Image 1 (tube, rainbow, N blue to C red):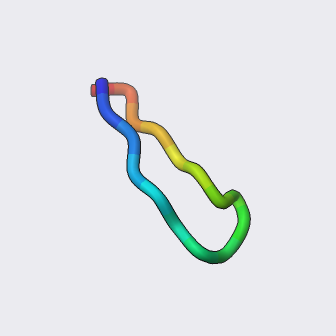
Image 2: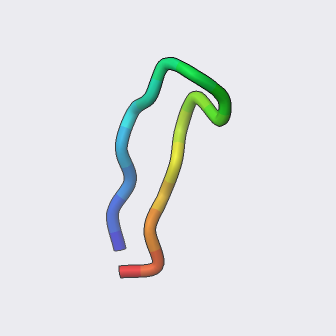
Image 3: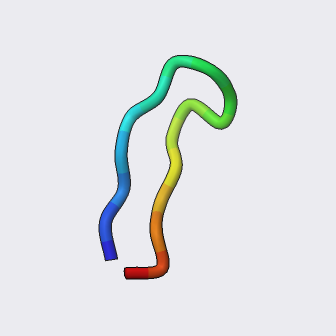
Length: 17
């Protein structure tokens, strides 16, 4: 239940937690 920022695509990724 949390996400994080990233440079390469996808620019934004999330988690099932």
